[PDB]
Structures are given as C-alpha cells and as structure tokens.
Amino acid sequence: SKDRMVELLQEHFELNLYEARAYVALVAFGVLTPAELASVSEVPAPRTYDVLRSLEKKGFAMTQPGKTNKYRPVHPANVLEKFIQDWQERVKEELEAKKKAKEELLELMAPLIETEVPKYGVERVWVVRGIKNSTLKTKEMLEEAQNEILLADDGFIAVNLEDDIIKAVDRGVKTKILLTKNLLPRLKASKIIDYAKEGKLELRALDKFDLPMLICDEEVFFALEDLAARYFNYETQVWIKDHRVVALFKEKFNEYWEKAEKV
Amino acid sequence: SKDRMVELLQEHFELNLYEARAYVALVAFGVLTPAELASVSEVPAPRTYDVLRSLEKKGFAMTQPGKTNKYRPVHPANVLEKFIQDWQERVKEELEAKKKAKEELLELMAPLIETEVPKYGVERVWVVRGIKNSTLKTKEMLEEAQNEILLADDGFIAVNLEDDIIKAVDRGVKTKILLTKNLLPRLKASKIIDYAKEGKLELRALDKFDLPMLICDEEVFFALEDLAARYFNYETQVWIKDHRVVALFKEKFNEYWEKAEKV
Amino acid sequence: SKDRMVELLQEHFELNLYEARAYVALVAFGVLTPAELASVSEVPAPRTYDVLRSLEKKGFAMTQPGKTNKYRPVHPANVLEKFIQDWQERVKEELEAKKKAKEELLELMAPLIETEVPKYGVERVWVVRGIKNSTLKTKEMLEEAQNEILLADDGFIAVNLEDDIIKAVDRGVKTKILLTKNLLPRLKASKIIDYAKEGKLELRALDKFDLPMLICDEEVFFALEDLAARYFNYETQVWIKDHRVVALFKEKFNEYWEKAEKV
Amino acid sequence: SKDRMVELLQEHFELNLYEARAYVALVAFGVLTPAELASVSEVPAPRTYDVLRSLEKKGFAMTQPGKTNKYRPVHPANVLEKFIQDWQERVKEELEAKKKAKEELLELMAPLIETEVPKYGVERVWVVRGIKNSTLKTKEMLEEAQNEILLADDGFIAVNLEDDIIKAVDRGVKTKILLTKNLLPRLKASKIIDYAKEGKLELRALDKFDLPMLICDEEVFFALEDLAARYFNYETQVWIKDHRVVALFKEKFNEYWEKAEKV
DNA sequence: GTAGTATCATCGATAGTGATACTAC
DNA sequence: GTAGTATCACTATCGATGATACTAC
C-alpha cells in the first residue's frame, strides 16, 4: 500500500507526510514536475515546489533546474541504505560524546559525592524555646551521640537526662559531666554518680560557669541567657551543627573542665 | 561547576532542566525530601514531586521501602554507565527496525520499479545536491559501466563504492583509478589491492588536481565548486550523458593521469 | 497601596505574585510564621511555607528554624539596593560575553563574507529546451558579459545574436567569434564581419568542430547532441557557471581557435 | 562553524533558530529570496517569509522595493556592533526604572516602618542563607554599633560596607579589622587604610584563620560551613545577640588578633 | 481550473507561575 | 480547624509540520 510506504518513510527515515508522499509519487511515476506531482498525489499544489526541493537536499531526488524543474527519485535501495549508514555514524558520534560527558560529570561530582546521611537534614541550626522541645532535642543529641558527650549544666538538664545519659555511655560514647556545686545534692544515689565512681563516665563540679552547653559529636546546644523568660519556660535555646563552632564551644568546655574537680 | 553538570545532564543523559538540577542536588546533599529540594535548589516547589518521581523512574534516584518522602541519588558512576549501556541497546534495536522498514519498502516498491525502462530514462542531465549525496548517482554509473571507468576521486566521488568497482572490473570494464595521495592510506584496507597489482585495473596517485571526476562509458560526473554552497551542504554536482562532453573531461583526466604515480 | 507595592516587586525585582505579597506582609507585620502569613495575606496557606523559604534564599527574609519557623523581612533599602547592584554585575558580564561573541562571529564569518551579488541566484546549473528559452539565456549571457565572449557556433548567428554580440562588443568586452566555414556566406552584410574588419572583434572559421559552445565570463552554454531532437527542436542544452568547468571548455575553444581564420 | 555561528546568534543576539540560520545563509550567499533560503538552509519554506521579515525588523537584513522579495545581509561588523550598543542603552534605561521603582517602594513602605521601634525586635537569633546575603544583616550590625566592632573578614562578611565602618568609627566606635593577606592588596585607597594610620582604627593582616566573624557590641555574625550548601548558594549564616556567646567569639577574635601584623 | 507566489494554523515539549485536594491529627 | 502533605492547572515560547490565501494567467 502507498499508505504503508508513506508510513514507513515517516517513521524511520525522517521525512514528513508531504515529503514522504512526494517520494512515493516520484518512485511510482518516475519523472515529475511540481505541477505533475500535485495531479498524481495528495501533496498540495502550493507545497509541491518546496517539498520536492526538500527531497532534493535530503538525497531522495535528483533534479533538472529550468523554467519548470523536473525531478527523478533516487533509487530507494541507494538512499534508504545511505540514510541508515549515515544515521549509524551519528549514533557512533552521539555515543562517544556521552562517554566523554560521563567521564567529565564524574570528575565534576567527585568533590560532591557525599556518603554522610543527613538526619534533619539540610538544617544545621534549630531554635527551641519550650521545656518540652528543649528535652526532645537533648534526647536526640544523646541518642545520635557516637563519639563524645560534653555536658556543662546549670540545673535540671543533667538530672532529667540521666536515663538518656546512661544509655549513651553504655554504647561506648565518652561522657564528661560538669555540674555547678549547688546541683550536687540533686544526684543522691543517682546512676550517674554510680557510673562516675565506677569509671564509666567522668564527673566534675565547679562553683560557677557563665556558658553552660551540651556538646554531642559536632553538635552544640546552648541557651541565650534571658532570666526574664527563663522563669517563663519560653527561654530561647539554639542548636548548631558545625565543626568550627562546636569546636569553639569545646574549647570553652575544656576551660571549665580543666578548672573543675572530679567527684 | 553546577551549571556545567546541569548542562551535561540535559544534553547527553536526557534530563530536563529541573531533573538535571534535582539530580545534582540529590548527589550533593545525599538525601532530600521534596520540600528540602524546593528550598536549596532552583526547582519550583510544586514541581519537586513529579521531578523526583521522574528521576526515580529514569533510574537517577531511589526511595526507601519505608516512609517514601525522602529521595537519595543513584551514584553517578552507576547511573551514568547504565544509561549509556541501555541507550546503546535502544539504538541497536531502532537499527533493526530501520533495516526492517527498508527491506519492506524495497518490497513494496518492487512493482513500481518495473522495466519502463525505466520510468526515468532518455534524460541525459541530472543535478545532485550535496557532496554527501555524490554516490547516490555515481553508484548507478558504476553498476551500468560496460566499457570503461575513469575515476579521479577527491574522496567523495565514489566513497564506499569499491565493491561495485571490483564488480565492474569483473565484467570486463577497463578501470583507471586516480587518487589524491591522502586517500591511499585506506587501501590497506583495500580490495582493489591486490586487484590493481594483479593488473585487473590501474591505480595512480597525485598530490593535486582541480577537477575531480567520474567517467563511465559516455557518462561524466563532476561537482561544481562554491564555498557558500558547501557550508550549507548544497554543493552542486552534475551528471551528463554526452559523448562530446565526456570526451572533453576524458582529455582532462588523461592530462591528470600522465602525471600521476603508478603506485 | 499594597497592590502597587506588589506590582513593583514583580516588575523590577524578580518576585512572583506570592513571594511579592509575602515580603509586603513581612514588611507590614514584621515577624510572621507561615500560618500567620496566610492570615494577613492573599498567599495560599499551602504555599506560604515554600514561598517564605523562597524569600529566604532570595535575600528578602531572615528566619528562625524551628518546629514552627518564623521569618523577619530584610530591610527594603538593603535588599532592593543589593538586587540592583548585583543585577548590574550580571549585565556587566552578559555585556562582556556579547563582545567576545561578536569578535568570534566576525572571525568565523571572515571566510564566508560574500561581496559578489548573484543575478541568477543560487543556481549554477540551468537546463534549457527549445529555441525561445535558449535564446533568452544566450541574450542574458551576452548582457552580463564583462570580460570575454568565446563563441564557437555550429549554426545560427546572426540568429538575433548579431545585435547582442555587437552591443556587448560596444561595452568593451573582448569577443571571439568562431563559425563553421559553411556559415560564412550567411554574414556577408552583417555588422559582425563589419566589426571584425575594423576590427572591433576577432572572427575565425573552421571546417568542423564537434563541441560548439558559448562562453561568457566563467559561464558556459552548450548542447547535448541528440539525433535528432535538434529538428524538433527539443534538444537539451545546459548552462553551467563554474571556474573549473568553464576553464575546461575554454581550453577546448582555444584548441579550435588556434585553427583560423575568418578570411 | 555554521552550527557555532547559529549557536552564538541565538545566545547573545536574540535570534531564534530560524532567524540565526537565515542570517548566516544571507551572509554566505550575499542575496537570497525566501525560496532560495528555504532551499539552501534548514529554515522551513513556509517560515522563510516571516523569518526574513523578522531579520529585517531586527536590523539583520534589508529589502529592495521589489517587485521580487530578495534579502541581503547587514554586514556583521555593523549589525553586531549596533545590537550591543543598543542593548547597553536598553539595560541602562531599565536600570533607571529599577532605581525609580526602588525609591517608590521605600516611600510606600515608609509608613509601614514606623516606630515599633523595630518591627522585628526582641529577637536574639536569626539565620541568613547564602554568603551573598551576608551584608543584608551585617549592615544593620555596623550601622547600630555603639561601642565596639571586631571584624575578621573573609571577604564576604562586610563586602562594600566600608562606608559604614568608617562612619561607625566617626561616632566613636572602637574598630579592629583583621584581614587575610590576600585581601589587603585590594583596599586602595582606602578610607579604611588612611583611617588606621590616622589611628581612628586598627588594621591587621593574617595568612589564615578558620572562623571569620563580625562582632558589634553584644552581637556576633558567623557563617557555618558545608560544601554542598555553598554549591547551591545556601550556606547558613547565624546572628546571635548574647553577651556570653559574643564574648566567646571575642576570645577567638582576640586569639586571631594577637598573631596578625599591623600592616 | 491551472501554475507559483506568499502566508496561516495546529501542536507537542518545556518551563515557568497562580492555585487545590488529600489527610492525621 | 490546624498543619501540614501532595499535586494541579494554566500560560508562553518555539520549533515542527500540515494546510491556506494571493496573483498571475
């Protein structure tokens, strides 16, 4: 069928409907002029000229340039195979590009390939105010703790965390507890003081320090001192995850720690 | 350069702008929820979902069997290599489809191409556009050559037509082949060698000649010369069937041939 | 009016409708949360979250990351001014790009710059049949002649050509007329023999030549000898414009021409 | 080449695919009718007309009164130079519009920013995304500085804020500026350099310090550090107003400051 | 109606950009 | 209701491609 011939030329050889109908006509009728083509095909008369001129450049037709151009079809066995061979050459190029593209992309993404898995995760700063949320955040910090826990506490933070502190120490994370001397009686026969006497965690006391902090593996949790709101459980507290910043606080802690006294 | 990565992905790996961005984001942050992606990247918030699902579908990102709100990138080393290997398969199959379409067309058109003889005949001049289409006519010249074949190849007059030349030589056609010296390197790597050294034909090389041509019996094929035309793959080539015109060109060929090397 | 404020932010500072309404809201109400933003603006509740996060990256808002994020507007005098200067630097870049682009384009188009103006067009091959069109083409050739006219004629002239040959010769174009001896008596009172004797043009006679031709300034006009379409007279004739081809015929003409004379 | 030209034209000179091609064709063949263009080029025949008219309008081609429709290219040296010069004009006017839109917005928002005193106040921690937006906060820090300013600039903490620094010094704020040695070579003249020799401030250079910062009274501004974040212009910067936290950072500054050179 | 010129119209893919639906409290 | 989530629908550009005037007769 000519319908089938037209379909195939469109589907596999990059000819539009009109160009395809034209080339079939040229093959069926041999030599045609734009005028003749129109009479023996469904190619619109107005379009015959450019459509045939289109087959010309694509290699499906040869031509005689004159007052009225006449066209002959190239032999389908020559052009169709030519098309395929050329196509394969394009493919062969598009392929090599893809490989060089791949090689380069891997070189570009080299520095970015990240094994670490974010748990929050794009967030490295978190602002907490309530007493509920301040505890839920310390809980997470102690749970995700894998290396060291440094706790300089002015009050309830260390007494309420005891359950969570113990569990962490059990996993093998180095724990250092630093309290204000006035808070000691709050730890009567507590499992912390028990662990401290065993050697499973370091415990020390200081009369005072101005910047209490919780440190967990490059995570620091501190408060913005407001005694006004500190009565109001709505005291602002900040969680920051960064090697540099947390390292700055760790220095301060070590300053405290090297001046305190173990129980 | 994130921009270069996005560019490459869009070009050689069939990702849209957003998907390309999303993948680099995925590769960068290791894990991302749709909202997180909308934040750190330039992918429209409302598009992050379909963009991420799309990447997953294209095998560029994965979702855990758990709460599927988080997406992780597939490692570039794996995903990029897999795309290229898979792509080769898709093209290879399209090749088969194309070949099947060609063979079918040749079959469908068989009845059309009968001894007429043929539908296009008695025409002694045709024009062919583009040096790339040179062989679409010269092939016919070689298949019908009965007496003599005189080729002064520029490297495009009779590309990949060697089989027809040796076939012509077999049916008793005298063949003189004149090549530019830069062509010889692909006779290694030939079939006319050892068909030339056998004496079944002649082969001579030459540094420079201004009028490359193919003569077959009383037919001459030559290309015109226009810088602008060739930039647009539109160079004009002419086929003339005339004993006087051919004879003139043959005088020029002979001129070239008496200066060529017997190599 | 806020409508006016929103209009300006969209028009000049690259904010969509929602982001623009948000920043106006933030400026009006100071600190807002996504929920609050919705209550005091026409920003859809579902969109507030991502829209505010958008103003964040764009530099129109600062934020407190928490269970419920709160946002403050950057001061319009800082952001709006910041935007403009940043924009100016992008412009400064796109400009430098444009200049380099131009420089390169001029280097690429250097070989392509065409001064000559085609009076026929892209066609360097023309196929003519009949006497009407072959004469109109010879006339055009003689009119456009500016350097030399080489005419080896097998018959005709002054078949309308005396007038055109003379007029050309009047313009100062070197003319060479070559007729077959049998044609000499046809021009005994012709203006050509008159001009030849003066001699404003060279005239010579030959008993025979197999390839008559008209040459005009790198244009050649010849016939494809067909027994006996010349009688019909549907004899195919070809016009070719090309230095190489025309030089080939010119060599042939000189072969003829070196065999005089007009007498 | 031709593909590269088309690429440039589309990129830097605001031509669509067809117009860019058409222009290169116009430059190549010197003159072209819509049909001729449709033939030699990849511009769809039915589109050649509007495409050529378009090129003319954009000042890339010119047309004769007819009767035929032939187009000539404008010389690239002229058209390309004209586009760029005109473009500079176009942007320069949009800049004015932007400045005018800004000035108006500040006016419209003036009533909004009334004595609250600050719309946003009593807030002691804010986050700012992207190093590019650093000054959108630090600016406020410097303009409100009453006692002390300690800058350890990385080159982005206080970009283009020199005027505010010298201005702060005038109202009696003690100013210490610590810069990396690679920054100093670009401080010419400047007001910050002949303010130190005058003694109105101090300036010390240092090869390397890990924690660039800005301290103003009881306020600190510092940036976190994440490669992935910075690739997406999403780096987190923090502003904290707390005497204990700032004092800590100040200890670090003083550490940096005791190793720098007086320049 | 016929030749040959110039001109329009429909559509898919992509990327923006102004809005809803579903859902567990 | 509240606070989220998960998608929707629409617009504009453009390059592809099929159809249709106008002007000669």
Image (spheres, coloured by chain):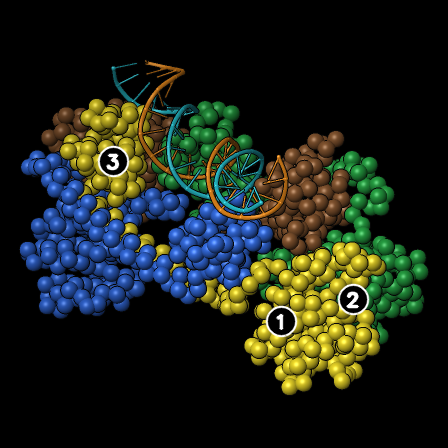
Chain colours: A brown, B green, C yellow, D blue, E orange, F cyan
Q: Secondary structure at mark 2?
A: helix
SS for tag 1?
helix
Residue underneath mark 3: C20
Q: Are marks 2 and 1 in contact (CB under 8 Å)?
A: no
Q: Amino acid at mark 1?
A: Asp
| Residue assigned mark 2 | B245
- State which quarter of the image contains the C terminus of chain B: bottom right
Q: Amino acid at mark 2?
A: Val
Alpha carbon distance from label 3 to label 2: 78 Å
Q: Quadrant of residue B13?
A: top right
Q: Examine the image and state in which quarter residue C3 appears.
A: top left
**Circle 2 chain:** B
Is residue A69 visible in this depiction of the protein?
Answer: yes
**Which residue is depicted at the point 75% across and 74% down?**
C186
Look at the image and tell me whether residue D4 can be seen: no
Kind of element beneath mark 3: helix
Q: Earlier in the sequence, mark 1 or mark 3?
A: 3
In the rendered structure, which amino acid carries the disc numbered 3?
Ala
**Residue ID at (86%, 43%):** B115
Residue B239 lies, in percent from the top left, at: 75, 59
